[PDB]
Amino acid sequence: MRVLVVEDNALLRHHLKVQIQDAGHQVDDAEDAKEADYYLNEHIPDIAIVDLGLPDEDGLSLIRRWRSNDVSLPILVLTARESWQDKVEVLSAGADDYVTKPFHIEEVMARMQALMRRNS
Amino acid sequence: MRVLVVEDNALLRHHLKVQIQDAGHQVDDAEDAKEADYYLNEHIPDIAIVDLGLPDEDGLSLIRRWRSNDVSLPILVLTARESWQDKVEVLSAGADDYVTKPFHIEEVMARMQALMRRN
Image (cartoon, rainbow over all chains, first blue to last red; front, side, top):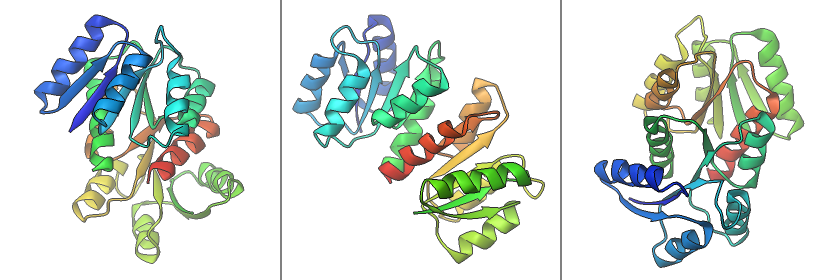
């Protein structure tokens, strides 16, 4: 499967990509929202991991905009924000799931896997 | 649409049932694993909400047994467990998501909707 990772922190972004690659997937890694639009349009990914703290455009704005254009793939959010209202808001904007920071990387892998399993 | 709630605590079960009804779905509410199997055999729900603290058969076993019998509907687990390793195990069992107890009902409604939306 093809995974799009959108993550502003270079080190995290690279870690994500190599772990997901090592599990047998192809990964596009974008560092901001507009770059995310770049990968989205070039190859439709099967799944996207989106950090909300993008320097470009907030991740919620990004999810909203994709959904409102009938982009329907599963999206797993990475987020600093962790109140229960934040989580309702994120889900309500079109995300399928979220992981709160700080996180272990095996937690994102496990969430991504569960969406992949459902999706396919 | 149709929701199966599996919850050993009568009050939480009753409360869950009416919130979900208030959002406009029909709800089967089961007390333990065997009663869950009863409803599942009656109607395939669009989703099952499964608390793990069942007296019958612990939630995870239930979910593993369902997955192995090709029951593939979305499952949102309710759990008390804390460890980030414990959370990961439940998804490994076949669950799609989980909410920790205590929770706000709005969180559970939002997770159920996210799953019905996608499926």
